Length: 334
Ligand SMILES: O=C1C=C2C[C@]3(O)COc4c(ccc(O)c4O)C3=C2C=C1O
Image (cartoon, rainbow, N blue to C red; front, top):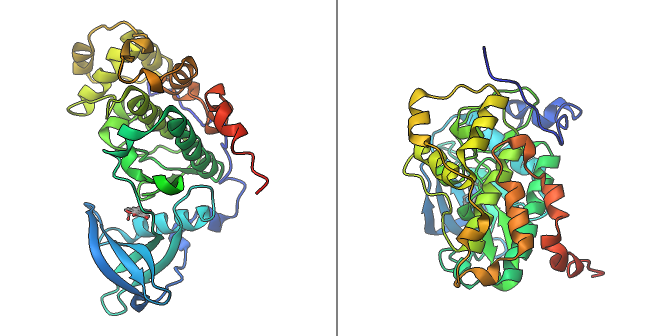
């Protein structure tokens, strides 16, 4: 017998009641801009399926970021483009400013707004309790928005959250693994960075939903308030579930698997062993305690749950008392 089917408990049918053209990205016709508007300045990063450059728009001398998409299935390129356009103008969603191509070689490239990112491996060291709450709330705005628009990000991690700290400016980037949610659809579990993979991915439960992103966010939260980056550090996908089991415990893991009738690789049960559930307080020490509060642990504890159906929605998260001080301070008359 197979696994129990599942569906999202929020935003379940958003693509169902939207026009075909909204989610049918294969039929999207790209509106191409002008490649000669942009000059490459320096290479920023080497993706495995792209390269990213700082660049200037020479029509207004504004910095931008250009991502060149070498070979790759056109269908993947169209998915990212349709998702970026669907989401543009959404809170803290990176803005796709242009789409261009070599008119001769046909090689496509995405142009994004420039964000003067703080290093991250450095930034988290200097963040205050208030700073983390503020930026968590901003990330949640992005996730609630893209989930409300029927899209799963599927690659939430600190590298995909650009933060211009001196402008209190946050953008969620890298929508290259993002996908439209359709209830009942069996998805590829080969998404997210190892450290931020939800348990559903790690046990090959394919019928997942937006709640995958909330696990990844939980992992980020833990790493920030406990000053341990990344928080769950497995040496591979199997080990990664072991690192989670050693904190959340094996009993709730086995209840999860049992609830969904999931069927585990035989050798999993040998390396999972048996582990009690650990109190979050066990990770609090002199050096990170100023970032930790009981509201923070209650909040974290409601994100990091095996059962994807059990995790907070972004909307519920935003209502948590952890964010009380940032919500008062954000009600802006402008
Ligand atoms: O799939 C991707 C991938 C990236 C990687 C990357 O190109 C890196 O660097 C960026 C950026 C966006 C804005 C920005 O300011 C910046 O520095 C990125 C993306 C957006 C996407 O949808």
